[PDB]
């Protein structure tokens, strides 16, 4: 899917996760690409992969 | 006495690094015919030898 | 025109991208074709709106 | 094994990624899987264990 | 007589390996492995220089 998640846009696949990362809502790689995000409601983590 | 006998090989996909899987970028990249081929041949043949 | 090759098969696709009729033995990188019918996903912070 | 533990544990360095792990995406991609998405592939050491 | 005969038979397997008419039986000895290694190395020189 073509996504725009917390104002970061791209194309990838979204999955559910297993992590409980407490800090922040967007997680990025060194290149800057979006690796995951959190829903500021329940708090679930999701992952993003090309 | 210590002597190094190997260096860990690394290969890079030229299209993915430069265009990040964007379908329009890779189409423009294809005019750079001699660019990716030189890079990929250099890294690949080093690993084979 | 001497000879042509259609870029339709998997081996011919690799030959077309490597831009040579003969390909040496080895391990070559490749990327599958992206789907074009692409849904849209949006996540945003609820704010003063 | 003293020469492989007294020396620095290079967990931030070159390690061949488990590609069966990365695309499953059950957890946020680690440093090795992050490199894989940008086209960088580190191959297993030729001087195997 | 044996030293000469084994030498002469070795040369035939070398020349035929360079041409490739014995390519299906090039693993019969690690002496013929060096012929495959040399041809592998030469072809890189002939191609990579341009
Ligand atoms: C130098 O290279 C030569 C070959 O160019 C090596 O000769 C090979 O040595 C092995 C081990 O002795 C031989 O294999 C064994 O042969 C015996 C008898 O047939 C058999 O019982 C074993 O199960 C195994 O097959 C091999 O046939 C022989 N080949 C030739 C062409 O002589 C030699 O070992 C190398 N020497 C050094 C010091 O690196
Ligand atoms: C904002 C929100 O409620 N998000 C999700 C909800 O959609 C999902 O159905 C549920 C399952 O545990 O977890 C939470
Ligand atoms: C989920 O994460 C936990 C904590 O890291 C780990 O123990 C477990 O192996 C993970 N589960 C799967 C199925 O990968």
Image (cartoon, rainbow, N blue to C red):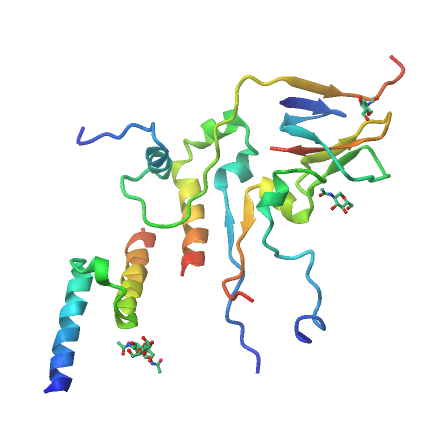
Q: Is residue A35 left or right of residue E5?
A: right
What residue do we see at 18% from left, 68% from top? E14
What residue do we see at 87% from left, 12% from top? C49
What residue do we see at 53% from left, 63% from top? B7
Q: Is residue E13 above or below residue A49?
A: below
Instruction: Name the spot of residue B10 as percent of width and height, x first.
Output: 52, 53
Q: Is residue C30 left or right of residue D12?
A: left
Residue D28, picture quadrant: top right
Picture quadrant of ligand 3 = top right
Q: Nearer the viewer, residue D49 or A25?
A: D49
Instruction: Name the spot of residue C1 as percent of width and height, x first.
Output: 18, 28
How many badges with numbers are in the image?
Answer: 0
Residue D12, picture quadrant: bottom right
Q: Is residue A2 left or right of residue B33?
A: right
Q: Nearer the viewer, residue C44 or D30?
A: D30
> Farthest residue in the left direction?
E1
What residue do we see at 61% from left, 38% from top? D23
Instruction: Name the spot of residue B41 as percent of width and height, x first.
Output: 40, 49
Q: Is residue D40 above or below residue E13?
A: above
Q: Is residue A2 above or below residue B48?
A: above
Q: Is residue A2 above or below residue D43?
A: above
Instruction: Name the spot of residue D30 as percent of width and height, x first.
Output: 69, 46
> Farthest residue in the top direction?
C49
């Amino acid at each position: 899917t073509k996504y725009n998640i917390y104002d970061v846009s791209g194309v990838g696949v979204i999955r559910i996760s297993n992590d409980t990362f407490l800090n922040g809502i967007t997680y990025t790689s060194t290149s800057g690409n979006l690796l995951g995000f959190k829903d500021v409601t329940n708090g679930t983590i999701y992952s993003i992969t090309p | 006495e210590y002597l190094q006998i190997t260096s860990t090989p690394i290969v890079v996909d030229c299209s993915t690094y430069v265009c990040n899987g964007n379908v329009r970028c890779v189409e423009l990249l294809k005019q750079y015919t001699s660019a990716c081929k030189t890079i990929e041949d250099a890294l690949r043949n080093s690993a084979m030898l | 025109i001497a000879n042509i090759i259609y870029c339709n098969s998997v081996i011919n696709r690799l030959r077309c991208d490597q831009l040579s009729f003969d390909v040496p033995d080895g391990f070559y990188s490749t990327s599958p074709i992206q789907p074009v019918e692409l849904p849209v996903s949006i996540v945003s912070l609820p704010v003063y709106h | 094994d003293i020469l492989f533990s007294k020396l620095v544990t290079s967990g931030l360095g070159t390690v061949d990624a488990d590609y069966k792990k990365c695309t499953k995406g059950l957890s946020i991609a680690d440093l090795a899987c992050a490199q894989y998405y940008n086209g960088i592939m580190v191959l297993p050491g030729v001087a195997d264990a | 007589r044996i030293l000469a005969a084994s030498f002469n038979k070795a040369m035939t397997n070398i020349v035929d390996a360079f041409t490739g008419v014995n390519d299906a039986i090039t693993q019969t000895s690690q002496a013929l492995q060096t012929v495959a290694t040399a041809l592998n190395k030469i072809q890189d020189v002939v191609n990579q220089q341009g």
